[PDB]
Image (cartoon, helix red, strand yellow):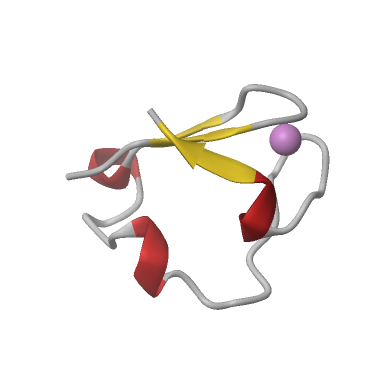
């Protein structure tokens, strides 16, 4: 499934580590656990 990376802190969202929930299905207000930015600051990787 599609991995996403934080444009500020490079935190990797790997769906394998998040219950195989796709990034686009995470609640809208989900934030980067490191730098606190919103999902719109993530790029596919
Ligand atoms: Ni971040």
Is residue 44 positioned above or below 36 on the image?
A: above
Q: Measuring 70% from the left and 57% from the top, which residue is drawn there?
A: 31
The x and y percentages for residue 22 are: 29, 60
Q: Measuring 82% from the left and 37% from the top, which residue is drawn there?
A: 35
Q: Measuring 51% from the left and 39% from the top, which residue is drawn there?
A: 43
Q: Locate residue 40 relative to residue 1 in the image: left or right.
A: right
Q: Quadrant of residue 16?
A: top left
Pick the residue in front: 30 or 17. Answer: 30
The quadrant of the picture showing ligand 1 is top right
Is residue 35 positioned above or below 41 on the image?
A: above
Q: Locate residue 4 relative to residue 2 in the image: left or right.
A: right
Q: Quadrant of residue 13?
A: top left
Image quadrant occupied by the N terminus: top left
Q: How many marks?
A: 0
The x and y percentages for residue 34 are: 76, 35
Pick the residue in front: 41 or 29. Answer: 41
Residue most extreme to the top: 10
Is residue 16 positioned above or below 21 on the image?
A: above
The x and y percentages for residue 23 are: 39, 58
Q: Locate residue 6 relative to residue 26 in the image: left or right.
A: right
Q: Measuring 63% from the left and 65% from the top, which residue is drawn there?
A: 30
Q: Locate residue 45 relative to residue 36 in the image: left or right.
A: left
Image quadrant occupied by the C terminus: top left
């Amino acid at each position: 499934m599609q991995k996403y990376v934080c444009n500020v802190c490079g935190y990797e969202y790997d769906p394998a580590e998040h219950d195989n929930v796709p990034f686009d299905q995470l609640p809208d207000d989900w934030c980067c656990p490191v730098c606190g930015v919103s999902k719109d600051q993530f790029s596919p990787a």
